[PDB]
Length: 289
Image (cartoon, rainbow, N blue to C red; front, side):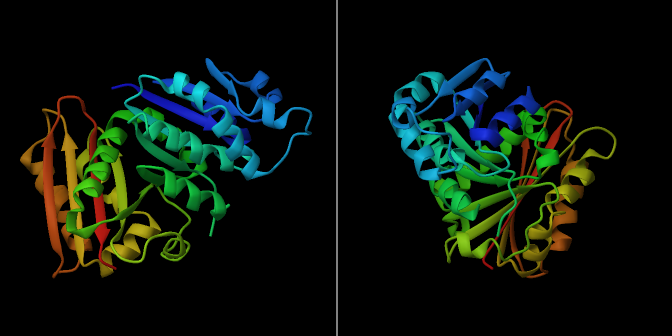
């Protein structure tokens, strides 16, 4: 399963540098690509921006990516999964990144929008959400977990992709959360569809306490904790390797069931996947707010 991680504009180029599975750096400003450690580098919109001073316009970023679509395709060629981020800070990349997402999706890569940028900015987030399979919000200091935990992460996004295709429990729209994120239930509504939106908490753990640890993590964020209480329904999944016991599975199931309403309809699922080793991953999707 080939994963390709793509940072776009100033913030994504730094994100990718921090992270250095294959990496691609994309920028409308060619100068910044001289500071890139990524093996694959793409200047986008060279003809569009020729002679211009460097700029902050997202629309330029967007039109630059459409001009360069062909070169982006070749670089992404052969990816099963694509992470796209513009990282921190604003610029052309917030315009460019959703196009890069859309391009990958149409090559049939499962496509995750990764948002490290604080918001309630949202101009960009709204557009990324429109363009991607699943959108994940993760804190900037935690960015490394997406590439360290890439295997459990990808199982989480595959589940999120599957819920959305089959409209499970009526879910037409979804945002994933990992780690402790600065959003409350507002900041979220204004950017999400009004019926059948959902929230996916994700947590990943290894070693001694791994099952209870991972379940607590998936519900730990401000967004998940406030929204499990109201939830009309909850989809939970735990995925582990050959070593995942019924004990671990039942224990994690318990922890989630308690946070949820006594009257919630919970779907509970358990997967033994030898691909995971000693890692386990728990996903919690609340819906019906």
